[PDB]
Amino acid sequence: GPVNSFSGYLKLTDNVYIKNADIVEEAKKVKPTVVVNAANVYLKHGGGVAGALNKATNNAMQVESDDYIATNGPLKVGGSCVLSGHNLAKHCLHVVGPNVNKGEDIQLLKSAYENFNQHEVLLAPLLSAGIFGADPIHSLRVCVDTVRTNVYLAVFDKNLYDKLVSS
Ligand SMILES: Cn1c(=O)c2nc(SCCC(=O)NS(=O)(=O)CCN3CCOCC3)[nH]c2n(C)c1=O
Image 1: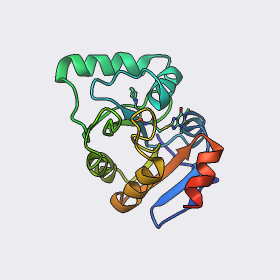
Image 2: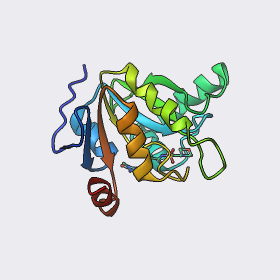
Image 3: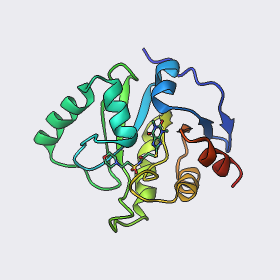
């Protein structure tokens, strides 16, 4: 099924690549095995990457997520769960980064990125780097130090992308 046809990425380390792109648009071109969603524990995909991914699935992601959460209860911070990737990928790895702004432990960003290690290749965003308030430079550094498998990072904003590549 999935083909993982990534292109245009800058190689930062042996297993970490980065691109200035829309993760929804990357997922449609790449057709990856796994696309990562930066979620909350209730899998309510209200905005950011999660809202954008859900919209691209025509709200199917939210319906499947609501069914999973009503059954199995919320996730743990730093935890994750594999659901369907719908039309974007084979699977979607919903990962919950810590809500740094609301006082959750930023050390859980290591546990959040350790969920990546169960998958050979992933298309992902920077965890907790949206409204959760984690410094994206710090989120990238935890990603590099923690992820051992192949991760292709999409950063939407160009200015932040240039900051990240230069750091
Ligand atoms: C279109 N598009 C974006 O919009 C976009 N945003 C980012 S920022 C990093 C990801 C992020 O938001 N992580 S988070 O802070 O943990 C989300 C917390 N939310 C709490 C409410 O429930 C949903 C989850 N990167 C983006 N890329 C690459 C992109 O392509």
